Amino acid sequence: SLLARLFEHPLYRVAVPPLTEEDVLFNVNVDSYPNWLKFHIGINRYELYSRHNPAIEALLHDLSSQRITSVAMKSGGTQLKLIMTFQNYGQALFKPMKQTREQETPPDFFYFSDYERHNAEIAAFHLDRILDFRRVPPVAGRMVNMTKEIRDVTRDKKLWRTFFISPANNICFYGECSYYCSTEHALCGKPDQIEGSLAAFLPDLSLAKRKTWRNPWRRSYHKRKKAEWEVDPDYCEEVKQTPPYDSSHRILDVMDMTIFDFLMGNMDRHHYETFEKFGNETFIIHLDNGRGFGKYSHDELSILVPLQQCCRIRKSTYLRLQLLAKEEYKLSLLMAESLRGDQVAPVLYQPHLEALDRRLRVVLKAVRDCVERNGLHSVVDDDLD
Amino acid sequence: SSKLQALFAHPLYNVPEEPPLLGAEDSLLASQEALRYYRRKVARWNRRHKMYREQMNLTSLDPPLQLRLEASWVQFHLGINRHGLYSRSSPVVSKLLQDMRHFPTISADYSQDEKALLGACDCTQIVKPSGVHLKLVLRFSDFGKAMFKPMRQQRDEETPVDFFYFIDFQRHNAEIAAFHLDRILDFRRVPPTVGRIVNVTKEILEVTKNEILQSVFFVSPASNVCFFAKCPYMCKTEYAVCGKPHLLEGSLSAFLPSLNLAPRLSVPNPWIRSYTLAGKEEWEVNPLYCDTVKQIYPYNNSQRLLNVIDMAIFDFLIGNMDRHHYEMFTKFGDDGFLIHLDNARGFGRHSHDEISILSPLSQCCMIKKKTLLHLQLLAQADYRLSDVMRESLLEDQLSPVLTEPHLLALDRRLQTILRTVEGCIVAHGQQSVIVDGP
Ligand SMILES: Nc1ncnc2c1ncn2[C@@H]1O[C@H](COP(=O)(O)OP(=O)(O)OP(=O)(O)O)[C@@H](O)[C@H]1O
Ligand SMILES: Nc1ncnc2c1ncn2[C@@H]1O[C@H](COP(=O)(O)OP(=O)(O)OP(=O)(O)O)[C@@H](O)[C@H]1O
């Protein structure tokens, strides 16, 4: 009900502009379609899904319960990511458990050394949902049988040949990616089931190409090397005068993203993707959110530097971010409830839900530091039609 | 009070050892030759070190190194006799351990065994050779050396289940504890080992002449001086080993004499493991495996096989599955004692007893008379194995080196060894289950 009241609020019923044939993604010139397909044909210019869509909550149910028919390991490398095919032709990306729940990434780990936990992937969907951004593909947790749903249903000999039995008579496997894909990192169930996050598959690039931009606040991805924006305090004055980032609808998309990343601690947003058929005047897809929620006793302020430098925010999210701080609409109790139905719940160790609020007030206080230094009407854009 | 003193003051730890040593041919190092060799290595070090200081522009302050006979490692080397590595209740070893804990370091390298790998990272290799592991060799002001194994795990941490032996960690505290167990058993076979807290910057990085070793030191987002083994970090199989921010604790293991003075013989154990994710060796399946071993040279003399039995006991007490090879001193012959060099893996499961280590004793069913007496004694409460270990380990700067479940495991594992000796006595009699040789 605390969550049910959030969506009764008048900040969460502002509809998107009227759509036209050049604003949808898949013009349909549709009730037996699977929930993954309703999800695809509903992607418009300014969202990934509707606020009260019947398919998104049903697609979440599918990823958790639907039977798995084929599994394949992803191409190239970059951490262990598995593609799964269900009985309804639908696909989903899978990130296995890899790390615990009450655990923290050690302080001595750089941002490029961190794990990818299903926790952050599941949580990021709900957090992106509570903020009414709706820029993440739906993801649900699941307790997968690593025999009858991984090994015994894959023809990828590269994967299959890593399923070994452990000294503890447990079933292990490690795959063949680039980072953390050897026996010492082999994911192991007791005796034959781990958990992961089935992230729903975006539409195939065959019928929906997707741009991929380099975020101008990407880190050096190198020790002992700074990334310019760590040396220029008004580096944002250059980005507001670059090829596309000079448009008002674009300099803002990054702001909503960074407030998202800082709430989770995801300092690995080196690139972001558009939708091509949509050009430069759309939303930004929040993908690969697995490097968050790895620290609960730490708030990484370096993530928020894009907001501190540009000192601009959307009034849409500003009035939201305030409401999420009041105890009657608190991020803690809202997220903990939204994450109560995920089959893998509790998806978040409690102090992360608590930290989620502490991170909100430092974002909220950061807007105030921009508002008394640059004024109000020059920090908040307006949305009220 | 003090069960430890009671142990060494017992009639067992005092009776002369047979056969006695004539000398000269029962001290693996010849004095006049060894001093000349070491005196030359000291002269070459002084030369090639001053030149390094001149290239990097550093005033050659202080005099050059002096090789003194009174150094601990010197007297440690010249004291290695046919009866073991060190002497029983030796005052040199006490000084030796204290020296490795306090003397300053003057050099640090990568050791051979690495370095001789040339390349060589094969991120596909599951059991990469024992040269891609984090360990350095330090040199002290008295010219002595020591194999430094840094801390890799907390005290109350075990090798997680689903971890095979070949990927188990490399505990510094178990290198120390294995030495204290060695001295308590009067096996006298692993080199003396101390725990020490090392300023990784002042005592490793700032003293190494190796351009690669300087390249593996970095600083964390928490501002801690870290370093790493070049190969495992690239394959992402292990992490780094950071100070807090500079202070790091490790285990120094005293160096054996130089292989130019005392050659050694890396011999494959007869009970090696497969070292694969599957597949078992012959002994892992045939309870009559030792019937075969007893008929293979040089295990036919019935005196080398006994030394391996002692090793199996010592490894079972510490849970050291990874004993693929035992080294020997060639001067002492087929009957010479075995050196227990790298124990860094034992003491990783305090809740589990791996009986496959005891397979030599289980299947050969024969134990040395002396070894059985010390094991029987260490089962009696007045000198129980855990208490004499707990007390002996208190003399280390890294106390407590062993948590309580580990110490209590030694007692229980001792019963299993004694239960097997008495157990397989019933099938063979004290005739073939005790070898009271001199
Ligand atoms: N002047 C130098 N410039 C650059 N690198 C050097 C220099 N001198 C030595 N090194 C590197 O450091 C190491 C030198 O170690 P050190 O001089 O302490 O003893 P060593 O002679 O190499 O070893 P050992 O004592 O076993 O003969 C060499 O392996 C070499 O790679
Ligand atoms: N306590 C110990 N634990 C493990 N390994 C040891 C120990 N003592 C010696 N060793 C091994 O013995 C070897 C020492 O020989 P090394 O190649 O350093 O030549 P050296 O003995 O220094 O002789 P020189 O420098 O005069 O040629 C190293 O590979 C080291 O791994």
Image: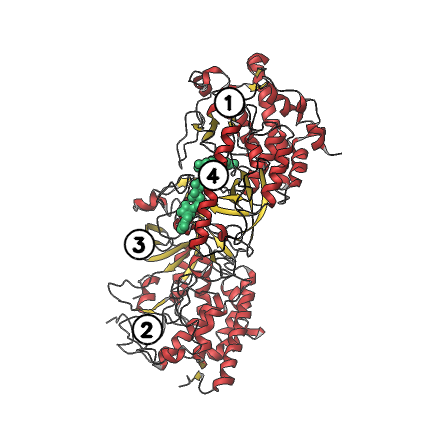
Task: Confirm whether residue A187 shows in the render.
Answer: no
Of residues A321 and B131, the one nearer the viewer is B131
Is residue A282 found left or right of A359 in the rendered image?
Answer: left
Residue denoted by label 2:
A44
Could you tell me how far apart the alpha carbons at marks 4 and 2 are, in whole angstroms?
77 Å
Of residues B370 and B287, the one nearer the viewer is B370
Against B282, is B37 above or below?
below
Asked if marks 3 and 2 fall on the same chain, the answer is yes
Asked if marks 3 and 4 fall on the same chain, the answer is no
In the rendered structure, which amino acid carries the disc numbered 1? Answer: Gly
Residue denoted by label 1:
B336
Dot 1 beta carbon under 8 Å from ligand 2: no
Against B142, is B248 above or below?
below
Dot 4 beta carbon under 8 Å from ligand 2: yes
For marks 1 and 3, give the one nearer the viewer: 1
Asked if marks 4 and 2 fall on the same chain, the answer is no
Chain containing the residue with disc 2? A
Query: Does dot 2 land on a helix, a strand or a loop?
Result: loop
Query: Does dot 4 land on a helix, a strand or a loop?
Result: helix
Of residues B385 and A162, the one nearer the viewer is B385
Chain containing the residue with disc 3? A
Residue denoted by label 4:
B41
Q: Residue furthest front?
A: B63
In the rendered structure, which amino acid carries the disc numbered 2? Answer: Asn
